[PDB]
Image (cartoon, rainbow, N blue to C red; front, side, top):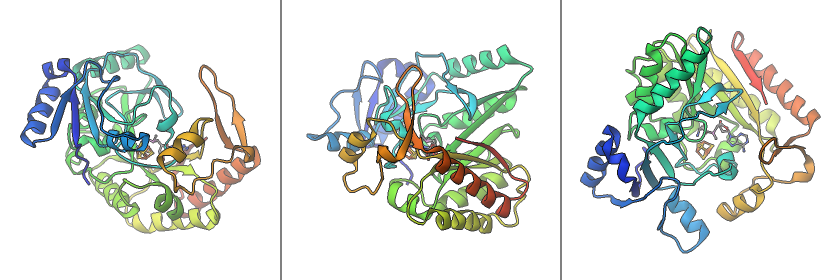
Length: 340
Ligand SMILES: C[Se@@+](CC[C@H](N)C(=O)O)C[C@H]1O[C@@H](n2cnc3c(N)ncnc32)[C@H](O)[C@@H]1O
Ligand code: SF4
């Protein structure tokens, strides 16, 4: 509030780049504990005698390295590609799908070689032109919540803004967006916020900004000319979810009244979890009310990795149909991009 790490690791090669040099100067000036690491994917000595201790301390650790995997992963249905600017998050959302993602790390990572990253992004744009290529920047992190430290997202926003056939988008649970308001986005960036019922936010989303904070930031970015959108996720069938989500869209409409919502977008994602979710989540959040009963769910099999549990077809349709009714009631002319 806003996030500042208690421990910072640096790859030695990171210091050769402008951002790495700038961060090293910043954190040494702040007197924060700094260590060295050979690879950002192999960080040693994070404090903690228990797994819970190491996990929580990792969430307060920043790692500064060089992106060496310049192949961009797909990020459908959100966008064509995931632009790799950062990985990990300081939040403690109980359901966070990044916890059980293959090769995920609990600590926060930022990449310094932005020239290489944007150059590769331009290559992908060139390969598909004159078709539009969309980039997701918050696929494996909360890029916005981290950005006050680096301004990497601001540079990405202004890079994409200068292109002809490139578009950027990202979604956040944080309100610390003041530095991005004067960015030359040029109408080519979709600034989104994750929203949910009061039940889900209060019980499952600690370490994030409040709903009022997210909406205050939503008004700022909209007022600064960004395309605005919302991601209703995870859509979770808690006790009283029907009324819970009704009141979400009602309150959302009240907090956005007066604004032009002609180009407003919605994305709907039902709660999913993997087979290793139960063991990991209960270890890290032992007092959680999160229901991970797999016998009530439908399993979707993985392609190259493992799959995940989602709600049964009839429950899923019921969620989709109900959410679509509320959006049409409170936001007519807003576009629902997908339900998954
Ligand atoms: C990984 Se989130 C990264 C972006 C940013 N840190 C943010 O939280 O908005 C991407 C979205 O997916 C949702 N989401 C997270 N976990 C799950 C899940 N297990 N099931 C279903 N949805 C899940 C989150 O609420 C986000 O709206
Ligand atoms: S804010 Fe997003 S990335 Fe961070 S823990 Fe919550 S769902 Fe995961």
